[PDB]
Image (cartoon, rainbow, N blue to C red; front, side, top):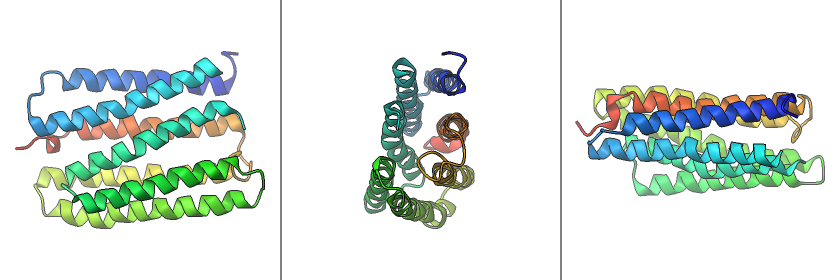
Length: 219
């Protein structure tokens, strides 16, 4: 069982999310600045949720085990968006629109994986991707304008986090379409690998970049 690739990628993801959570935890200890504390709270929570989910997948190890990963996307995507929103001091109206689109993206992707008719899979994938495209459009064009009018450290760190987010998030629909939920081109164990690397980079990698920066401070 432990020799199966699928199990291995799940074990590695669990270790990486756990390690990251704890590192963020230790890095956050001592930090007294109010604004910084907010980023540490959200950014540490993200990989903690994913750790819990990946662990549960291992404990439980088509195939209901992966619904746990989807549940982690549901919880973490909006938190990652809040992180970015807090960095650029985005207004509540745009934040609500982003989380609203995020809900559609997550919800329809799930529906796309449930459907018992190969054809509609891509219909739900198209709606979910359209929702993702809106979020990324807001982050790349909308948040950038606001970020550039702010402190150099904020504008600089946001651009890096922005590029990372756009690239990593864009990879999910691609992996889904070539995976078992889509066209079944890439085997399940390879797809499980891609989502894991994508998940860690998007949470731990994203978190490292953010928490290593002076942009989280009120200055």
